[PDB]
Each structure stands twice: as C-alpha cells, then as structure tokens.
Amino acid sequence: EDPPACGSIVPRREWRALASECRERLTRPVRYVVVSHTAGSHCDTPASCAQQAQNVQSYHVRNLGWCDVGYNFLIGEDGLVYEGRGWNIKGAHAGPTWNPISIGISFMGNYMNRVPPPRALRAAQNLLACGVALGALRSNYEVKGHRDVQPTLSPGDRLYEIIQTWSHYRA
Amino acid sequence: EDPPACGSIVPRREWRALASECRERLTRPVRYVVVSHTAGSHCDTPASCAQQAQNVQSYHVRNLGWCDVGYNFLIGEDGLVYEGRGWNIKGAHAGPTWNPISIGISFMGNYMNRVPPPRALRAAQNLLACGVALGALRSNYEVKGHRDVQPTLSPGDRLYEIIQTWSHYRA
Amino acid sequence: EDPPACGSIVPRREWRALASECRERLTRPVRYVVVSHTAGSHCDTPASCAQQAQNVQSYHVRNLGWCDVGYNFLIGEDGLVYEGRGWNIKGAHAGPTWNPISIGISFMGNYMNRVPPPRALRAAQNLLACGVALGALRSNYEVKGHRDVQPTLSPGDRLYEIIQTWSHYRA
Amino acid sequence: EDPPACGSIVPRREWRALASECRERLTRPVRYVVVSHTAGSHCDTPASCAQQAQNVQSYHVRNLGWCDVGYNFLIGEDGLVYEGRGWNIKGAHAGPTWNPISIGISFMGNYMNRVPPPRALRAAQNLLACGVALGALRSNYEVKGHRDVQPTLSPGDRLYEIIQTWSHYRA
C-alpha cells in the first residue's frame, strides 16, 4: 500500500461536465499514450479553460452523439489537467485499434503554428508520471503522436516536433 | 448502361498505386457519402496530382500500416478523380460506425483558407451522379461533412460551407 | 389519438397480460439495447407465443415479486414482437448498472443449441429500427449481449454468435 | 440478397416460391392500394401460411399460366406479410386499368363470414407505412376495396366493412 496524492487534476464536476454514459473499461496497466490537439481555440486561465473543456465535450456529445468527451484527459495552457474519461474508461480519440490499449491526452488549442507554453508541457509529463505511480500506465509506457496512428495533422507540427524528443516516444 | 455509363476516373495503375490488400466489402446500394480533405499539399496538374495520391497512400500503408489508402476516391484541383478503394471496398476514413455504411471522398489539399476550384467541385458532383447511376449509391443518398461524424476540422471551413449548399447534404 | 407508431407489436391486452405496476421511466433517447433469452420453452404460433409471454410475466410477477415482466419487449419464433414494459419504462433484465440506461429485448426460448428462425431475427431488427424512428433509441445505439454485461450464458451461444454480426453490436 | 427487412416481410425463398418470370415495372411513387382476399383456405401459423402462399402461387403459375403469383404482397392470420411481386413489379390482381397504377395486397382466406385477426390488420397497415417510407407509395395514397374496382365479393363483407374505416380509404 503506497498512496501517492499525485493528481492535480481538475475533476469533471469542477469544469461542469455533462454526465458520462460510457461503460467500457481499459485493462490496467496501459502500455500506450496517444497525444493529440483539439484544433480549437486555446485558453490560458482556469475560467476560460473550464469553458473550453465544456465546449469540446459539447461538440462530441451533442453533435457527434458520443457517450462523453473522447479524450481521457485534456491539457490547458493555464497549466492544469482536465479530467476526461480518466484512467479506467476507454476513450474515443485514436480509432478502434488504439482506443482499447491507450490513454489519449489532448492539448486544448491548435499547435501547427504555436508551441504549448512550458507549464502545459509540465502538466502533461507530470500527469503521465502520476499514471505510472498509480499503476494505470506501465513504467515502460510508449508515447505516440496522433498522426503516427491515424491520418491527421494532430497534434500539430510544433507540438509533434516536441513530443518526438520525449524519453518515452516511440515512432 | 452504355458500357462504362459515366465517370472520368484515373485508375489505380495510372497513378502508380501499390496493390491493395483490403478485402472487406460494402453492401450496395450505399446510403452515405462523407466528404473530407487530406490537409496536405494541393496539386493542379495530372502529373503532380498522381504524385499526391501516391504520397497519401504511402502515408496510410507504410506508416499507419493499412491495407490501402483509406479513402474510396480522391479529388484533385487538376479536375480529375483518383480511384482509391472504389465503390465496393470498405474504407478507413470516418471511423468504425461510418466506414461500413459510407463512401469517403477526399479533396487533395487544405480548404480552411481556400476554396477548391470549380473543376474540382464538378469532378466530385459528377462522381456522385455516376455512383447513383451504377447502383453503388442510393438515389436519395446523404452527404455528411467529415466534421459532422468525427472530431476534426476536415473538410475545411470553406469547403464545409460549400457542401452545406448541396442538394443531398444532411446535417 | 392517431399514433404514427412504427411496426407490428402484439399489445399487452392481446397477450392477456396482468396490469403493470411499474412507474420509473427511461430518459429518451436510449443508448443501449441488451439482448437476452428467456431460457424457457420456445413457441412457434401466435397462440402458443401469447401463452409463453403470460408464463414469463407470471414467473417475474408472482415468484420474483416484480412490478411487471422484466423485459421491454419479447420476441417469438412465431415472428412477432410481444409488448413488455415498452419504450418508456425501466426494465428488470441486466442488473442495476444497465437497467436504467437500456432497452432489454428477450427471445423466448433457449438458444445454446438452437438458432432462432430468420423471422424472429427480422422482427427484432425491425423493432430496433422502429425504436430509432420514434426517438426511443439513439440513431447510433449499441447492442450488447446479456453475457457482455452480466455473468450468464444468456442469450445462448448460437444467438450470441449471431448478434455479434449485427451492425450496431459493440463488445 | 440485399433488403435488410423493413416491416418484417417473409421473403420469396423463405415460403419456397417458384422464381418469378415477371418483367413489367410500376412507376413509383404509386397512388393506389387495392385490398383483396384469396377466397381460399385461411392459415394461422407460419408453417401453414407459407404453404398457403405456395398453393396460391401454384394456382396462378401452373394453371393460369402467369409469370408469378398475382398479388404484390399476401397477409396471413399468422400476423406476417408474404412477399409476392413486391413494390416494383406490376401485379395481376385488379384488372388492366388498375394493375399498372396500384399495389395489390391480399388477405389469405375468405372474409365474407369471418374477420381477420387484429395482427393481420396490423401487418397490413404497417406494410403500407413501410411502402410510404421507401417511396413505393405516395404519402397521400388511397385504399380501394377489390369490389370497388372490379365486379367481385372480394375482399369479403367483414373485411370490406373494416377497410372502409381506414384513414386512407376512398370510395
């Protein structure tokens, strides 16, 4: 019994999320993390980023008809992590081959022509360390770009270039 | 049917495509058409557009490990249609709910800030008429934007605005 | 009352059902359909299948003490659908996690060593199309086996194998 | 095959029908529906009703020398619809003025002194809704009795009295 308080995660309730209808679970420990971007507007305050998480969920639930926002976690330029489907529920973010064997994290913004600010990158890397510490991720997890597994520009040229330098990145 | 009975399509061989390994079939007549963009470079000559189709296939086959280019057909700004998986083989373009019940056509380019030239739009609309005439599509088929069924900017703001005016578009 | 109600369902009165005491409602549109079997006798005539629906209700009401037959609808090998709790009332068929978010349809018989006849399968698939058309089910609904959500042999090996081939099945 | 049901029709092969030789087509959308009875034996099980459809076809093909059973659809007291010539092929049921502009549905039995059971009537009304939904019938279609267009007792006094109460009936 080794309890970490590792999570500085904004919970669903705090960003005023609609209730999830999703039921399918991931088998922990998970081996893969897929990094994407939302390609929408960016935010840099907790107030605007909470609104942005709502908007992203609203799009996936109301328009696309999904059970919840597709990503397991979202990352703001405010420096905070927003709880999506979390560590235990299967996401809808990288297609049916990868969705069942991965955690999908998405940076809120468009990173074709912009880098995320250092605090966003810290939030993301720390989130992953927390995942390992809980047993949600494998200690030898592997990070993929969204474009490495699906046909897309995501996670953005600038952000893609960055994640390639990460220790756990695998092409 | 006066032999062919429609369509000026560049065949796989002509654009120098790798052989397809895909086996799964669509049930004709198909009800849905999903319009996307490649989000890559655009071309405006048969020589450059044939190369572009190769590049798109190369990405899907060599990197993503797919059986063939994901789209059923591609549209060039040269005014020609490039044969993808065609009318009969299931595509990999709009996820596992839509892939089995739809034809996916993709315009080669990024149409966020650009409209396709009239000849591209003609090629696409004519391709669809040919589909109905063959019995590949239902006479009352419905056109969706890629963004209407998956979380994405595709098919681009400008092109999305255009397809919304089409007779067969359904929100 | 002039209902534009889809499909040919045998109403409660016609199969001589006891009056329901159930009051709790589902939130439409519903996302999930759970397929089970009764594991009892099969019938292949309207006269015997009406009797079978009575017997199934009798068991759930008199012995198990439930407010009505547990299933929303039952399917006969006669090729007809028997009205259970219907589209709007919560069922008692797949436990307390799934009962409030699903429609439960049950085939009358034991399908471990037997397939339902084609007309039973048609009745069931048509019933579901009717559900979507009324707004009772979501257009992107998902079909689960009873065994996929509870520890059970239901809906039978043979029938389970069949529902796996359905378009809306999700594991 | 190809047709994924609609309102649960027993297909030609399932009732073991001889292959149709008919070639003349109706122009959809059709305006008229003529209701008749076979004036033969009634059946109330899928097994007996499948046999009855065979017998009716056998009479029209072997003795009368027709290309197929004359009716577009037949209705059983088992509660099921039997596929005749279907929605697109011209029937032989109400003479040469009406045959080219109508769908002919026939109840299997003699309804002079007998009413069809409610499930037969439901099957018929549902079949017609399916017709409108497919574009085979006009949304403002009109229902005639066989006796309203030809000199005959068909569709039987009891059944004639009933169809007169229908919303789309026109004298």
Image: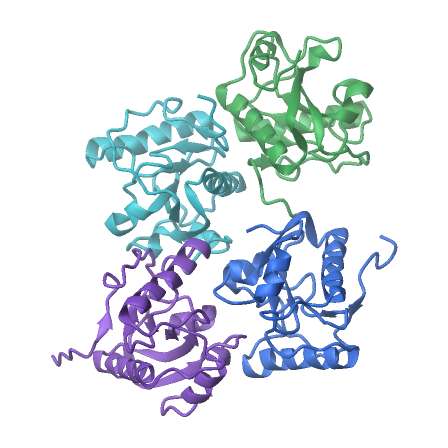
Chain colours: A purple, B blue, C cyan, D green
- Residue C87 lies, in percent from the top left, at 38, 37
Q: Is residue B82 left or right of residue C75?
A: right
Residue at screen point 29% across, 79% down: A137
In the image, farthest residue toward the right: B2
In the figure, residue B143 lies in which quadrant?
bottom right
Q: Is residue D24 left or right of residue A49?
A: right
Seen from the viewer's position, the closer of residues A85 and A120 is A120
Q: Is residue A78 left or right of residue B14?
A: left
- Residue A107 lies, in percent from the top left, at 38, 75
Q: Is C149 placed above or below A46 here?
A: above
- Residue B72 lies, in percent from the top left, at 66, 66
Seen from the viewer's position, the closer of residues B32 and B44 is B44
Seen from the viewer's position, the closer of residues A95 and A65 is A65
Residue at screen point 32% across, 65% down: A25
In the figure, residue C48 lies in which quadrant?
top left
Q: Is D98 placed above or below D112 here?
A: below
Seen from the viewer's position, the closer of residues D126 and B130 is B130
- Residue B171 lies, in percent from the top left, at 55, 51
Q: Is C39 placed above or below A74 here?
A: above
Q: Is residue B124 visible?
A: yes
Residue at screen point 60% across, 25% down: D75
Q: Is D6 placed above or below A155 here?
A: above
**What is the number of callouts on the image?**
0
Q: Is residue B15 left or right of residue C50?
A: right
Q: Is residue D52 visible?
A: no
